[PDB]
Image: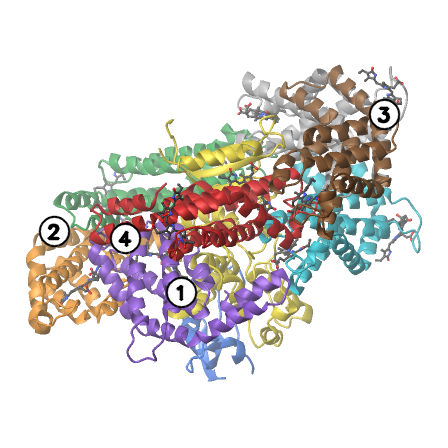
Chain colours: A yellow, B green, C purple, D red, F cyan, G blue, H orange, I brown
Amino acid sequence: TSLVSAQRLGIVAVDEAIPLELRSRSTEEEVDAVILAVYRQVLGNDHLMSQERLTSAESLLRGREISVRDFVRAVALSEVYRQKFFHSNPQNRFIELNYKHLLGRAPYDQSEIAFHTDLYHQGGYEAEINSYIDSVEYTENFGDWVVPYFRGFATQRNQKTVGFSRSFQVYRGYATSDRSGSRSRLTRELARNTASPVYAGSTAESLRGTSAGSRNQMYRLQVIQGAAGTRVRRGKAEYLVSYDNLSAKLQQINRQGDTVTMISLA
Amino acid sequence: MFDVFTRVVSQADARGEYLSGSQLDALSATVAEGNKRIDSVNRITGNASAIVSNAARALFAEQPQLIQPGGNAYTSRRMAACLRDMEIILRYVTYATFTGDASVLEDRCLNGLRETYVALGVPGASVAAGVQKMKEAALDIVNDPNGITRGDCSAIVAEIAGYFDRAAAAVA
Amino acid sequence: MFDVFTRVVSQADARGEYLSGSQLDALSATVAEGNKRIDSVNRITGNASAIVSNAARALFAEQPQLIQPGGNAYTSRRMAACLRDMEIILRYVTYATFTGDASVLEDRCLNGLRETYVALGVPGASVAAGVQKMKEAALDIVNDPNGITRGDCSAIVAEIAGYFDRAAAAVA
Amino acid sequence: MFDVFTRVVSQADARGEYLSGSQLDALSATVAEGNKRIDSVNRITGNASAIVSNAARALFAEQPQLIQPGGNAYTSRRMAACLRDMEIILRYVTYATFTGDASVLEDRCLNGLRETYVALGVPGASVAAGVQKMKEAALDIVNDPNGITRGDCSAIVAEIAGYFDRAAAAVA
Amino acid sequence: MFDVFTRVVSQADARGEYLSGSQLDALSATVAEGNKRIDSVNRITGNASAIVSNAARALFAEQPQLIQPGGNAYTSRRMAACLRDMEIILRYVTYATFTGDASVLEDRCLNGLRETYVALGVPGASVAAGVQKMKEAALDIVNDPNGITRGDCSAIVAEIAGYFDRAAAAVA
Amino acid sequence: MFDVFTRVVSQADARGEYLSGSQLDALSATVAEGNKRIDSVNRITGNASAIVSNAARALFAEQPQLIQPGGNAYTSRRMAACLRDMEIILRYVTYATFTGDASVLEDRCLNGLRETYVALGVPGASVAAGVQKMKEAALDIVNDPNGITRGDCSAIVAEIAGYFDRAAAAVA
Amino acid sequence: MLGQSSLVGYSNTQAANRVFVYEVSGLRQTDANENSAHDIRRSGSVFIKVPYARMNDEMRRISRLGGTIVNIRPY
Amino acid sequence: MKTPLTEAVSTADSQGRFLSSTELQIAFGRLRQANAGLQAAKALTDNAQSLVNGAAQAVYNKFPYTTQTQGNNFAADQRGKDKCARDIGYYLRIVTYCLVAGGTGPLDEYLIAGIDEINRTFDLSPSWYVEALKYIKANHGLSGDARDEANSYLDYAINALS
Amino acid sequence: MKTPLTEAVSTADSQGRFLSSTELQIAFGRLRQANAGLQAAKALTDNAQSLVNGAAQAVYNKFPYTTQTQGNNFAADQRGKDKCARDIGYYLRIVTYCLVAGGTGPLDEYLIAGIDEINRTFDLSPSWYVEALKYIKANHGLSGDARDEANSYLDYAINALS
Ligand SMILES: *[C@@H](C)[C@H]1/C(=C/c2[nH]c(/C=C3N=C(/C=C4\NC(=O)C(CC)=C4C)C(C)=C\3CCC(=O)O)c(CCC(=O)O)c2C)NC(=O)[C@@H]1C
Ligand SMILES: *[C@@H](C)[C@H]1/C(=C/c2[nH]c(/C=C3N=C(/C=C4\NC(=O)C(CC)=C4C)C(C)=C\3CCC(=O)O)c(CCC(=O)O)c2C)NC(=O)[C@@H]1C
Ligand SMILES: *[C@@H](C)[C@H]1/C(=C/c2[nH]c(/C=C3N=C(/C=C4\NC(=O)C(CC)=C4C)C(C)=C\3CCC(=O)O)c(CCC(=O)O)c2C)NC(=O)[C@@H]1C
Ligand SMILES: *[C@@H](C)[C@H]1/C(=C/c2[nH]c(/C=C3N=C(/C=C4\NC(=O)C(CC)=C4C)C(C)=C\3CCC(=O)O)c(CCC(=O)O)c2C)NC(=O)[C@@H]1C
Ligand SMILES: *[C@H](C)[C@H]1/C(=C/c2[nH]c(/C=C3N=C(/C=C4\NC(=O)C(CC)=C4C)C(C)=C\3CCC(=O)O)c(CCC(=O)O)c2C)NC(=O)[C@@H]1C
Ligand SMILES: *[C@H](C)[C@H]1/C(=C/c2[nH]c(/C=C3N=C(/C=C4\NC(=O)C(CC)=C4C)C(C)=C\3CCC(=O)O)c(CCC(=O)O)c2C)NC(=O)[C@@H]1C
Ligand SMILES: *[C@H](C)[C@H]1/C(=C/c2[nH]c(/C=C3N=C(/C=C4\NC(=O)C(CC)=C4C)C(C)=C\3CCC(=O)O)c(CCC(=O)O)c2C)NC(=O)[C@@H]1C
Ligand SMILES: *[C@H](C)[C@H]1/C(=C/c2[nH]c(/C=C3N=C(/C=C4\NC(=O)C(CC)=C4C)C(C)=C\3CCC(=O)O)c(CCC(=O)O)c2C)NC(=O)[C@@H]1C
Ligand SMILES: *[C@H](C)[C@H]1/C(=C/c2[nH]c(/C=C3N=C(/C=C4\NC(=O)C(CC)=C4C)C(C)=C\3CCC(=O)O)c(CCC(=O)O)c2C)NC(=O)[C@@H]1C
Ligand SMILES: *[C@H](C)[C@H]1/C(=C/c2[nH]c(/C=C3N=C(/C=C4\NC(=O)C(CC)=C4C)C(C)=C\3CCC(=O)O)c(CCC(=O)O)c2C)NC(=O)[C@@H]1C
Ligand SMILES: *[C@H](C)[C@H]1/C(=C/c2[nH]c(/C=C3N=C(/C=C4\NC(=O)C(CC)=C4C)C(C)=C\3CCC(=O)O)c(CCC(=O)O)c2C)NC(=O)[C@@H]1C
């Protein structure tokens, strides 16, 4: 997005990112940069140890034996990818990680969760992973030579609006990685076809004045509430409370049977 | 998505019963007015660029702070995004008009748009005002009596206006 | 995931000391229990389709409302997803039995299953009832005395029963 | 919240029929274990302070970075908050033991606790380690065979172990 | 909030260290600057209404679109809100100058102000322009040589400038 | 991101006004400082490995809980990740020095870093302590008068110190 | 001619342990790739190494984009 | 959910373009077909009970072993016969939905997807349902456009099962 | 953080008013005290090691049972002695912070709040820490304003513990 929304949302680096294309007759440093970009984006910005590097796959990429898409596929099918994104993760979290790493976006629909779940159950991890890389979406956006990059913050064709909002649930910042087993943030949002408010970068903070307590910190409590007292006006509720009233607010939410969806510093 | 027929179909399967005579006659009534629905879709489409541009000009005239430097419509990139959002909303309104159901408009366009605009800082009230101007314009083309067979399109006009109301409610 | 051995290893590495003698003898006792562990895994695996189908049949018999139109197991795809869920739960129970540790069952299957079900409207209590049906069906299969070397498999049966209960508790 | 009886009542009421003979017998079996359940609750309650203090000492010994300056348990105010959190988890685990159902622990203690610890910078993994320490001490105290009518309390001990695992899994 | 002394204290406590000789010497240097800091606070406070009023008049004179009908400063309530905002920014700048730390300005005033302004359509750039007007107006008042002991106030002028620029950066 | 020139350019474009004489003169003054800014970047870069290694050694000597088993800098992978974080922070501080603006730190290096450290359980205060060690070493290297043209580099050193402090406050 | 180590999936199907080289020509701008973010760099003979299990996909991909499969050779 | 209108919008939205004359002709084709589809569904609905019982009887006739062999998957008792009649009624009802919808979308969404898993895990022969669908074809008594569209849905189900 | 300046700003901010002469006099009083506080902090810091060791010995002398009775809460072993010296060092360091800050704010935020829950949970006698603070009072060697302000913080800790 433009700068004025980008600084607020903390997506300036994503907006100014340039797609990396491995051209013909590329030099050694270009292949090095392409390999580094693939490792950064497919492995979700983890500190990749040299012992976890795919030496044979990057050799084939260097020697023009395979394309960038094939190297992306080799990294995605690698046991390193399995260990940090599949073997200790629930299936819904795993496929949103696949969507972020391979297509650069958040899941659009619960049917996309229904897909890749049956596909896993019928054809294994390899077929399920190949679905993303062989998809029509991967071909027009990245092709055989462009490193995949995150696209959820920009308006795409055949895109649902929720994708942009849901993007901030899967991209938590430039200095973030997908490293810690964790559950998806999009489960209820995808299942019930909703959208969650975006609280990223500086968007989450709210005015404090003299209303915040001793340590001048407000917390936003997003809860799901029903009538258990006073009339409930909305199913969704947001509560801004100081630190000193955080335990009391939590306990009275608990005794009303209200489900807490999120707590963030505001 | 859902169209006017599949909505009744999905409700009937959940109840696990055949469509009754009344529902079948309601859908027969719906396909009786199918030609007017096609005309309205075609008429909005043929003047989509004029609808978007005239509504944007009116919106920037009534709200000069959008195009004022520092405004959210200032700079070519933001102005281009704004005109694209107007065209996008209009396109999805036509999609909902075509299908006879609002599912395409909600699921693909309207759901998540308020949060997106709040996160972007796009003024939802200004976008809602722009959608009313497109609504006002698009009903004038849809209700234009010149060069079309005479008939009563009040029902389809109300349906189109309802879709535009959903859009305006969603952005704000 | 962890197995019965790596679980002790990870705790020891975090504490930064070698496994004590007692931990080594405990793992050796697990080793002496290994053939019966493999037999139980093989027996549940060999009857897995029968286990899932019979448990599902019994579950739909006492809960006709699952398969009633509008029910959560109605329509072919939902019913197939339901049978898949039974099969998935049974498979990770066998994985947990094989490893001697519940981490694969917890991380891959049970983590997030409850709120997935709650979000989607899949009745977790009914899933728990189905898992309980697979429980005794598989425990009779594991404890079947003919065509196997005799011995006490009560400890293995208790461990497999615990995995099934953990799954039943997680989905509800 | 639900207790062991109201849990199956809630499941039956959704399904709209009476508790079957099997469900009533399972509940009578729960009634037959009630004395042991009251003993386990009583034994943990009588040693709550010992459990909390010993678990905290073991945790800060194994994870010294919690109590060095700049650590999250450093300063008296944060150490007291941490001891209070040990106390709150143990108390709600006993509530779950008393009711025979994990709903009180989930709805009143674990509801939003991981998100709360993330928002505050409290290390959830270290909270889970402390809960695991409380678990081992409490299960030992419940299994102590001195000064009590002897009997097999493995089922209630397994149930209590499950509540502690739920707490440890929710915080981390 | 922090003042100039407790900011250094909090950093030391996080490190678990006594203040070094250089930090105590730096604190002694800012103690020797305390009289000048009090004069700056006194001079801005004693001219606060004039600073706000002249800055606001200049801002609308150079940005007439704010006070034109439909503009964000149009109507007496929004005009009053704008003036109040100016006085609020200036007051927290004096708080920060008094304390010697921007924590009070950042935590109580600036945090979330940009989100509020974006959500309301308050143009942050013109708020930043208005704060910039209060900036040199207050800096010339602090630097007025008449009726005060002569001495170099360059450090305190630079610090107050930083608080003003920090407020301007937050709103824009 | 912005450099020292585009920062005032973006501010001016939001105001929709040309850069005034004072802004242009301030930028010219920044240009006369450019050689020393390039020298500071070059000196930190040429000693980056020594800065990281010495700072890490000092940090682990002061906080030995990090490197003992179970600590967050224990194991080679975790230690190498810690070393990479130190080098990455130093690299982005050089970027900020080179550009004259802090936006590269907020946009990239500190964008979600605190969230990352809380999620993984990395002690942020220890990271802030490590950043301070790199701060004192890098400022000493920049201020070394041997083998360079003599001059006053206090302003660039103060700016570099601000970048280091902002990184430390981002994680503390 | 290398590649089979990484192109063939880690599944040990004997059928899947077969890769083939596709020669494609005339990769034009068509209505199928109007919204392609990347641009076509070569329209002459390009060589794509395809494992057996993806030959169904790739030829479809080639056929939507106007490419002419002129030859297919065992690796 | 494959219907002419939803697919026209799906295609247009996938190309990010407004509905042109191509989509208008799609809607025109849906309009020409809709009345025949609606009369087809009504005729099947009014004749649903005789069609379902006759289809069940035809399957029992062609596969007599279904009525004396004991087993959960067979109809030798009343419970199996009830399940058989219910399944054929599901087939008949979802076909009427396709006639209402104008495409195989109801069949794809509600019946076709996962039917292979179901017939295998509960060892139901798809040949039973093929004969049931064949009986409905031979005895629905539709003519013209209604018959053609209804037979296409019934043949779509048959080809899915075979 | 209870400091003259932060509290002055806080009171003014709740009334929403600018800093008047009252807040300026608070700042003037803070300035009058601050240099003495800074030298008090420097003297305590330079003598910190002997003060902490001497305070620990005074507690061990007054309560000999702490060095000879087994238990986690006592200092009969090296682990307990290290914890004790660390606690007294914590006390001394936060007292220097108070002298720097000009108020009991560091003691309140870092040490005083929750200390009674600590001493109860870990069966630590507050009398031990009172004796340590009394030793520090008697041995810091400060005079004048430095002594008065430092004794105020040390007596504040003593009164909290008793
Ligand atoms: C309200 C929407 C306006 C209106 C509409 C209206 N149209 C018709 C009739 C027809 N219009 C069409 C449409 C098309 N034929 C084409 O080939 C194309 C391009 C693909 C289009 C858009 C058709 C086929 C008909 C039927 C034949 C005819 O020419 O009349 C009617 C008459 C009733 C009907 O439903 O057919 C009406 C009412 N008329 C108005 O007064 C409104 C301004
Ligand atoms: C596992 C938990 C341990 C265990 C328990 C156990 N307890 C009983 C029996 C009883 N205990 C009580 C308890 C109480 N009486 C009181 O007045 C109070 C205070 C309110 C308490 C806590 C009672 C009433 C009984 C029944 C009479 C009796 O004294 O025996 C049993 C016996 C079986 C039963 O269910 O009655 C058992 C097994 N025994 C062990 O070995 C574990 C270490
Ligand atoms: C830059 C800020 C200007 C400046 C300041 C300056 N002030 C002093 C000295 C004093 N100022 C005061 C202030 C007050 N006394 C009061 O009773 C009140 C009301 C509560 C106030 C605000 C005091 C007490 C002093 C010291 C005694 C004296 O009056 O001289 C100095 C002198 C050096 C010093 O810091 O003590 C300076 C430099 N001088 C300028 O030229 C700037 C325009
Ligand atoms: C504070 C930063 C220290 C300092 C710096 C300083 N440097 C110069 C002058 C120059 N430095 C350079 C730099 C380079 N030339 C190269 O080719 C390379 C490698 C690409 C570098 C880094 C240049 C070009 C100059 C100008 C020529 C000259 O040598 O004078 C100055 C002098 C003032 C100026 O701005 O030129 C200063 C002050 N000096 C100190 O004492 C600090 C330790
Ligand atoms: C070292 C001083 C301390 C420490 C560090 C530590 N960090 C991690 C893990 C990560 N560090 C980062 C940070 C970045 N990655 C980037 O790309 C950027 C530039 C924008 C930054 C700032 C991230 C994202 C991670 C996540 C994991 C990853 O592998 O990338 C670890 C590893 C933790 C673990 O392995 O579980 C560690 C150890 N730890 C200490 O104890 C020191 C105080
Ligand atoms: C114009 C009337 C108003 C306006 C608009 C504006 N919008 C954006 C940015 C985006 N718009 C969307 C919306 C969609 N994307 C889709 O794919 C769909 C269809 C399903 C929709 C509805 C999104 C997601 C964005 C952000 C991503 C992108 O820009 O591509 C902007 C730009 C904001 C910025 O800072 O760049 C603008 C300006 N702004 C006004 O002031 C008008 C009132
Ligand atoms: C059958 C006994 C009950 C039932 C099941 C049912 N489940 C779903 C949907 C999902 N189930 C899961 C769970 C998993 N998928 C995995 O891949 C893993 C293993 C790693 C697990 C644990 C998920 C993620 C879903 C959602 C995605 C999907 O649709 O497949 C459904 C479908 C719900 C819907 O269509 O909305 C059903 C029907 N339903 C019952 O009524 C039984 C009690
Ligand atoms: C101790 C094992 C670890 C630890 C703990 C720690 N927690 C907090 C702060 C809070 N803890 C809670 C949790 C609850 N409050 C309740 O009322 C209940 C029942 C619903 C629970 C479970 C809350 C809400 C807070 C914040 C508000 C409050 O304290 O009242 C802290 C303090 C953090 C801070 O002061 O900033 C600490 C230290 N820290 C560790 O390092 C241990 C692993
Ligand atoms: C004046 C230079 C510009 C301007 C201002 C303006 N602000 C508002 C509304 C609000 N301002 C605040 C800010 C604060 N409230 C506080 O308590 C504090 C301290 C923590 C601050 C900084 C808030 C919260 C509001 C909203 C609530 C309220 O109206 O009081 C308005 C009114 C907007 C509206 O539509 O009502 C205005 C006009 N507007 C300009 O055009 C100037 C450039
Ligand atoms: C009748 C042609 C033959 C027959 C039938 C029979 N069917 C079942 C069981 C099931 N039938 C279905 C089918 C569907 N469920 C749906 O939701 C839909 C889509 C809307 C369809 C087509 C399913 C899923 C089952 C299993 C679950 C259930 O019992 O409902 C049985 C019983 C099998 C069992 O093990 O209980 C039988 C007997 N039997 C014959 O002999 C006929 C030739
Ligand atoms: C020394 C005077 C006597 C003594 C000391 C002793 N203390 C502990 C344990 C703890 N001390 C504290 C105190 C603090 N922690 C803080 O962060 C601060 C504020 C900055 C204070 C004052 C705490 C929290 C503990 C418990 C946790 C920890 O170990 O840090 C012990 C050990 C008790 C135990 O059970 O482990 C001891 C021995 N013992 C004597 O005999 C002296 C007379």
Q: Residues within 10 Å of mark 2 (few under 14, many from 20)?
A: many
Reading the image, the residue beneath label 3 is: I145
**Residue B166 seen anywhere in this rendered image of the structure:** yes
Q: Which mark is residue D26?
A: 4
| Badge 3 element | helix
Chain letter of the residue carrying label 1: C
Reading the image, the residue beneath label 1 is: C159
- The verdict on a common chain for dots 4 and 2 is no
Q: Which residue appears farthest toward the bottom when viewing the image?
A: G74
The structure residue drawn at horizontal position 39% and vertical position 33%, both measured from the top left corner, is A234
The structure residue drawn at horizontal position 80% and vertical position 57%, both measured from the top left corner, is F54
Chain letter of the residue carrying label 3: I
Q: Nearer the viewer, mark 3 or mark 2?
A: 3
User: Above or below — where is B84 with respect to H50?
Assistant: above
Q: CA distance from mark 4 to mark 3?
A: 76 Å
Q: CA distance from mark 4 to mark 1?
A: 21 Å
Q: CA distance from mark 1 to mark 3?
A: 71 Å
